[PDB]
Amino acid sequence: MNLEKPDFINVCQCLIFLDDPQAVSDILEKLVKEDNLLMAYQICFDLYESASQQFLSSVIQNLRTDQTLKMIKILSGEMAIELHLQFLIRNNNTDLMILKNTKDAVRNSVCHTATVIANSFMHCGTTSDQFLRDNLEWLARATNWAKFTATASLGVIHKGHEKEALQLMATYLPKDTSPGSAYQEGGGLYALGLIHANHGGDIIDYLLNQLKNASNDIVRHGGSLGLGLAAMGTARQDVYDLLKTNLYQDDAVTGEAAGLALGLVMLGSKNAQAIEDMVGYAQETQHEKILRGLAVGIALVMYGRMEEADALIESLCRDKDPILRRSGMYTVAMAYCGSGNNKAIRRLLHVAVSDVNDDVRRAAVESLGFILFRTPEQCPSVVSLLSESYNPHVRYGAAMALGICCAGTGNKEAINLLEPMTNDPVNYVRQGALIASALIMIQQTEITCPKVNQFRQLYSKVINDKHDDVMAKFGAILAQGILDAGGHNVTISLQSRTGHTHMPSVVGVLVFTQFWFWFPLSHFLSLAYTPTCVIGLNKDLKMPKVQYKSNCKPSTFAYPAPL
Amino acid sequence: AVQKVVVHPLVLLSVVDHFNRIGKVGNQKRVVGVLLGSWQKKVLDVSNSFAVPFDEDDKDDSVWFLDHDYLENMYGMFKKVNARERIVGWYHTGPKLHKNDIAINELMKRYCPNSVLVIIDVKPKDLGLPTEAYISVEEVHDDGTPTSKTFEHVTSEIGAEEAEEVGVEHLLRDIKDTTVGTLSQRITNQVHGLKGLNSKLLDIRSYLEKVATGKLPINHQIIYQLQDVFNLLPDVSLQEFVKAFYLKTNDQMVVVYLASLIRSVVALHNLINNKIANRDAEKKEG
Amino acid sequence: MQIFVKTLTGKTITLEVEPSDTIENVKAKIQDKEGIPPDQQRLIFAGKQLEDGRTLSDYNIQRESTLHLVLRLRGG
Amino acid sequence: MQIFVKTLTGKTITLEVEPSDTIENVKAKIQDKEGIPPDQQRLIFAGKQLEDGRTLSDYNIQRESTLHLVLRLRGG
Amino acid sequence: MQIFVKTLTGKTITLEVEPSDTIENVKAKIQDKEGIPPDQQRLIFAGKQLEDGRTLSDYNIQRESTLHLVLRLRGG
Amino acid sequence: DLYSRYKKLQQELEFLEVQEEYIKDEQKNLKKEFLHAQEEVKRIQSIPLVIGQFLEAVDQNTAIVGSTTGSNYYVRILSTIDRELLKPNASVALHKHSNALV
Amino acid sequence: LNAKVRLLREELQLLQEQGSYVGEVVRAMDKKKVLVKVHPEGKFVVDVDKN
Amino acid sequence: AVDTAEQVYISSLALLKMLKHGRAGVPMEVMGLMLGEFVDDYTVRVIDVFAMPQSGTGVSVEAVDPVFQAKMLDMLKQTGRPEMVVGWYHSHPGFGCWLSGVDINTQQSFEALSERAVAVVVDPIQSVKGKVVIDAFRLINANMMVLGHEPRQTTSNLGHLNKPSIQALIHGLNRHYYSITINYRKNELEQKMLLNLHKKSWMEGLTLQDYSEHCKHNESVVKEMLELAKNYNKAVEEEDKMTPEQLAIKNVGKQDPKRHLEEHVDVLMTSNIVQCLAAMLDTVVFK
């Protein structure tokens, strides 16, 4: 600041690493005073895209207590949402042929639902219904819990299409068309949850009413996932009360729904009351489902707190009940996210090599990714040797730790290790290796890494074979949708543009891997797709036309797969 | 008379079940039930058991209430299912013998003359065995004091049979230990032994000190004679015994000098082969 | 000492009791004013499963606590 | 000497003790401070499980040392 | 005349009959209501196995009588 | 310049140290697993089994033997028996249930 | 070491297997059927596998 | 509604009871009841088992008289185990584990009377050495199969291990009934009454047996190791300028160093070190 000019770099990095919202609000006001508006706009866009929630709240409150409108709107995110949607809706150009093929090849097993998940991945954010519209006598073949997944899927197609949300959903008349199903009502609230992620906006005060009245079996499951999604990270006490009361009702199917949602709102708050109440209800209960909920719901309460969490860890890690020990491993994962701290590695390896119960060995070795992704060149050096242990669970964990460590970039050694494993005798480890490869190779063309056209064909082999195990082709038909996400226009990364760890992405991809225990959780991956584009602008209101020019390209890179 | 009792796992597990469940009827410190079993010859094998409703009072030992009719009915049904077992005795839990117990014994001794009492300590302890077995006999007591009835200890052991051990071994598969062990299991045993020995020696104090305080009367008749014997029985290092030094060295000239050596020569042989092969494979490609 | 019992039907019912009581007595009071058979009553407190054989003080229950009643539907 | 113990919820508790104190005496002291039944507690230093049959001098728990305590959140 | 039939699973089933009714008529009522073949039902009252040749006026039964039902279980 | 090299040297040193400790631990447990596996394989013939008589050998770890109850069979053989003892005929042992040659 | 223990475990897994009969063929048949003569007694019509 | 991939929790004690009773009447089949609780919408917990009077024969069973069963529940109820029955089990002496056509006719009555009652089957003489052959089943109704509807619902923990046996697959598997996953929830307390218990000692930790029984053992092992060593010397003097691939070529058996030389060393070291250490302890613990 003593230097000649104010700037971004100091105010971008230091004031949010230091968490000094007053200082940034002051320098922002000063930059308004001398009428240098372009700096004051660029700083807002730079800030929103990498500042935490609630930090924005204190900044906006200190500020407002004209330029006010055009700075508040760009500060809360509204036009960033608008612009992103407007990019995806125009650059969409998915190829329907693959869906037509897999649809024709499917037999009437579980793979049916595995189609309608992957479909929603590729048309994500694109607001286009075509594959669910041109045929319907086929989609009506779904029944029971499947109807919950399929009707939830609309929520990931219309991601961010916030403005009209409610009118759209009732436009399907889910409640009026027949009272003969509760699964549709159960799905509706889940879809509203997916559309408004983080932006609880108005809809919190609508869901909070709608959850009050319930055919308590299913409607409360949908409702609590939706409400736990819309309001995440805000620590709002009035919500927490209602989720606690639903949890204490002690019902299996309503268990882990609240078990998660009560964890999302408190995220990172370290709240010393919630931890003691939740761990106290995890002991001395007798339904596994509720434990499989709280196994996640606990860990998210601590986040980046690092050493200031240790005390809970070496308590929770001693418990006899295995689900608690697994949740201990998830907690030591989230505590140190991105931070290559050695002793956490030492613990995770000791557990993975020693413990007697396989699921904690999986969840141990799997979490190595979350604490190493700052240096993806290093992950293969450690996980490689694990990939040959005799018991399958450790192999599955290894494959997924690779998929989650190197996620964004086609690092060659990872593919080099995954190649042999795609033909492991044990079905579910093939299910693992396929999805890991698909994550790690999103948007890669042959010139940028060589192996792609191996894998792009291999899936269509498996999915068309008929002498194979169902779960393998499940993993394949999911990988298709992973590889062509959002009309090729979106990518997965945990690092932010400038070195910050983007929390929604970590949360979404962590809670994705639970697809092992409950299928409708797989949609939670959609939080991780970030658009990958440059927006030309000259005034917030004004996108003027320009042509950029990309040198040193034969023009054979970029948009792939027309053929 | 009996020289030893053999207890099967099934009774132990059923006793744990009883003690956990009893909270469903009314809080109690301990539980009581029948033991069924059989006689081979002076050895007694126990193989089943069942609950019986029982109640007590915490202070007055004159008050308690067992139940005849439930006992007879249930034994009738069990006999209708199988005929080779018969009544043999009874068990209770709680960690220490209660004064009351003899009064119970002289009851159900009527159902079997050689009623033996087994105490099973359900909550854990580190030092050793879980169970104790006792038999009731009168005595000369002294040169001259009234004859009475008390128990004496009889040695006890835990048994097994075909198709009861297989279920146990399956249940215990997750946690396992080396069958023999190679200096990692024998060495631990010695430590455990020293723990037990020190436990007993410390327990002697809690009696002998408080009798020296005069808090309780001297049991002159028995204890002191045995503890004169004890202090008599240790040994001593007396120039003649240390001449059996000539045994340590003869262990070592079988260990050290004739087992280490042929453990190094093998390692040199392996190293030579390794260097040969690795250098050969190097120059072959060059 | 009043205690609030909540049913799955949405009803809250207030029973005055004393700390010396025992769970079967409470279930008897329920059978009194609910009319549901005491054997058909199951009571959960904070996730724990209460036993008919014990005292309130065994579960540290204080004034105005909430207990949840659940029925058994095996008779379908 | 004064020493500190930490627990699951993160509360830090201060105890004044003498080197010849045995672990059951420490249990009695801490239950006097907080009423926890002496069986519901276990204490840890470094990585090894402390056991009752020894004095603090045997482990040489230094002055102001930090201990971890592990417990069920309620006795039932 | 209303009667109660219990079963080993806890299922309870009320039924209305008249003392002129013969036992096989009762087993027929059970069959049609539950859906169970008459061969497979066996009936117990007060510890005596009932028999087809007799009315409920025999065995001096009264209303609100608790009968028990047991299945003809077999294997091979 | 030299500061970055200094720091990176420190980091990679300690990290390979961590790997070293990991490998030692995994060695220690694999040894126990191997011991236990041999223990299981040892108790596969300590059984009151039957006598057959060797008839023919097809290929490695596989043969044809006619049991004394008629009903000529075709079964694997154990991996520890010496091969050069069973050419023309012999008194061989057959598992009671699986008829595996021991 | 890992390879060695894996091999031994697999062998133990394989030894837990059922036996098979040996039979004399008297003639084949059409559409994947054979006529065999099991040793103790019997004259069966059996099906072939895929290999 | 429809079923999914659920589970059965059986207590350790009930497992011991089933094994013991099944093995008792070995030449004939046996059957009994089992008691527990439908704790939620999709797990089932069995706590205890008791037998009943039965007219066994080498291939079938029937229960004799009902009064016994009606009584014993009323007895158990007044000593703190009120649970009603949840299902039944029997045994197959020598065959595979699967349901006969008469077991269907038995089962239909329970299913008609209670919606979820599993049926359990045990094999007492294949469970010989270190494994148990126990399984649990339920029926599938006939007409639903003709309709497009399949038996159940799917979530990813269906497919571990649960490869059906070919022997079972020959009978009505799937076509007539489906298997259910089973696991043994051994809670605390009963854990220790087994682990820390079936094997133990106290004073046995300090015993010497220092007579000839030791020296004779040494003078057997070293004596035979003399010949082992001479063999190895001869077996390495070849020193031919060939390649260790050719060594593997002719390698068949009796690989001296590893095959025998080393285990003798390990045994001798173990025995002598332990003996000397124990003597050195007793020389100080007692006077």
Image: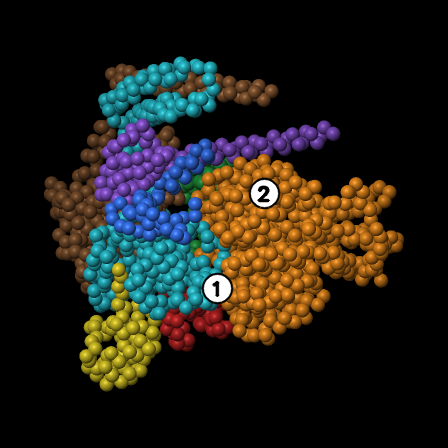
Chain colours: A orange, B brown, C red, D green, E yellow, F purple, G blue, H cyan
Residue A309: which disc? Answer: none
Left or right: residue A203 versus residue A111 is: right
Q: How crowded is mark 2: few (under 14 residues within 10 Å), some or many (20 or more)?
A: many
The image quadrant of residue A195 is bottom right
* Residue count near mark 1 (Cα–Cα under 10 Å), binned few <14, some 14–19, many ≥20: some
Instruction: Determine the image quadrant of residue H276.
Output: top left
* Apparent side of residue D7 relative to residue A561 in the rendered image (left or right): left
- Label 1 and label 2: CA atoms lie apart by 37 Å
Please, is residue B73 above or below residue H237 in the view?
A: below
The residue tagged 1 is A251
- Residue at figure coordinates x 29%, y 20% from the top left: H224
Identify which amino acid the numbered label 2 is placed on: Leu
Q: Where is residue H50 in the image (x, y as percent from the top left)?
A: 27, 59
Residue in front for this viewpoint, A270 or B87: B87
Q: In terms of secondary structure, where does tag 1 sit? A: loop
Residue A332 picture location, percent across and down: 56, 45
* Chain of the residue under the numbered disc 2 shown in the image: A
The residue type indicated by label 1 comes to: Asp
Relative horizontal placement of residue E71, taking residue B257 as reference (left or right): left
Judge from the rendering whether residue B142 lies leftward or rightward of residue A102; answer left or right: left
Residue visible at 84% across and 58% down?
A542
Tell me which residue sits at (33%, 40%) in the image: F75
Picture coordinates of residue A291, whole percent (x, y): 49, 55
**Residue B199 seen in render:** no
Residues behind callouts 1 and 2 on a single chain: yes
Of label 1 and label 2, which has the lower sequence position? Answer: 1
